[PDB]
Length: 125
Image (cartoon, rainbow, N blue to C red; front, side):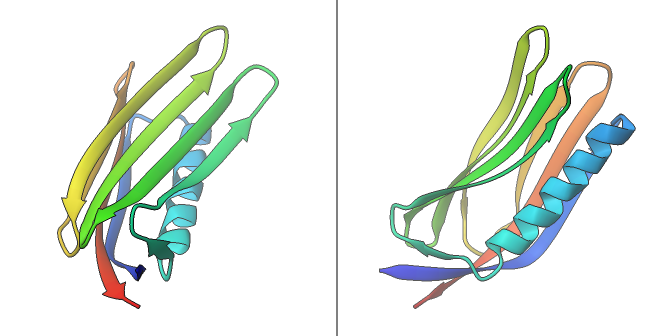
């Protein structure tokens, strides 16, 4: 069976970000908001939305994964991966219900925080 998602509420904020990090985060957030609104997803289906910054010295990939675990029930992961001299990964996984706000947060060294808050409508179709 299928559901159609809609973004009821959405808020992406950040602290301590460098200009390029903030640009990337805002672009990711807008991409996520547009991709999730009107998204059709099947029971048990996992989807992923990603945005990447590539430069010769470093790559930054932000990914949001969403799984329709059961009726009105979701599992999401927000993940940041930086590939430089070494590779750093930070991520958070949350389980939440349709119609309730969920918050996902990434914290990095030097006072950097990425925060995503959203509320999903799940319409049976």
